[PDB]
Length: 88
RNA sequence: UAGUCGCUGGGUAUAGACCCGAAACCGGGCGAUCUAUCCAUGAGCAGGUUGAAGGUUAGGUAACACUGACUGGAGGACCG
Ligand SMILES: [Mg+2]
Ligand SMILES: [Mg+2]
Ligand SMILES: [Mg+2]
Ligand SMILES: [Mg+2]
Ligand SMILES: [Mg+2]
Ligand SMILES: [Mg+2]
Ligand SMILES: [Mg+2]
Ligand SMILES: [Mg+2]
Ligand SMILES: [Mg+2]
Ligand SMILES: [Mg+2]
Ligand SMILES: [Mg+2]
Ligand SMILES: [Mg+2]
Ligand SMILES: [Mg+2]
Ligand SMILES: [Mg+2]
Ligand SMILES: [Mg+2]
Ligand SMILES: [Mg+2]
Ligand SMILES: [Mg+2]
Ligand SMILES: [Mg+2]
Image 1 (cartoon, rainbow, N blue to C red):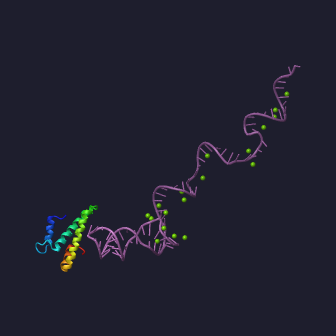
Image 2 (image 1 turned 90 degrees about the vertical axis):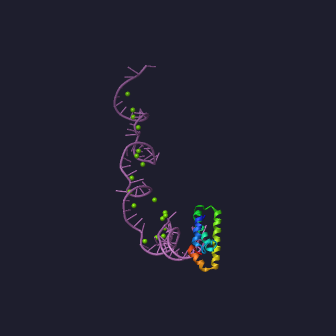
Image 3 (image 1 turned 120 degrees about the vertical axis):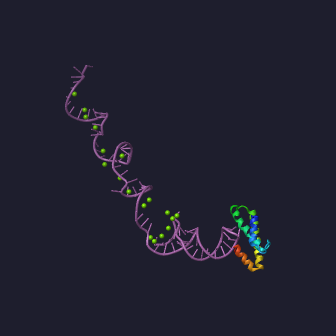
């Protein structure tokens, strides 16, 4: 549901090596933006299970990436959790 | 082959007709200061319990859900 401009400004805001789209932080930010964006769509369309499957897949991907990042570096983990405003 | 009109008595008819005695029917009125409903305007209900919805907060959820604590004061509720 994201746009080209939205993704570009997200990666610009969260890039860590001036051209890295694969670092955990960028992917986590993109997934969080998409999850937050799809909420209002699912507010109106409660009977759309087929898309909610993809939403759950994105949630699982974000969870796994956060777990890996926490396992690797605690400081970057805490910083990312702080900026994204999510519990854990 | 004598009837008529009085008077006095015994009967009869129509009248309450020897006297007392119903439950009832019909007509015009009087009553909702009792009581039954209703309408307007007032006032009365000591004292003590229980504790719904809701709210706040801390968790928790992708989000809605869902838990605890505090609060709150419902009811043809409870004891009197
Ligand atoms: Mg004579
Ligand atoms: Mg005579
Ligand atoms: Mg006589
Ligand atoms: Mg007589
Ligand atoms: Mg008589
Ligand atoms: Mg008698
Ligand atoms: Mg009468
Ligand atoms: Mg009377
Ligand atoms: Mg009266
Ligand atoms: Mg009565
Ligand atoms: Mg009154
Ligand atoms: Mg009282
Ligand atoms: Mg009541
Ligand atoms: Mg009531
Ligand atoms: Mg009653
Ligand atoms: Mg009662
Ligand atoms: Mg009682
Ligand atoms: Mg008593």
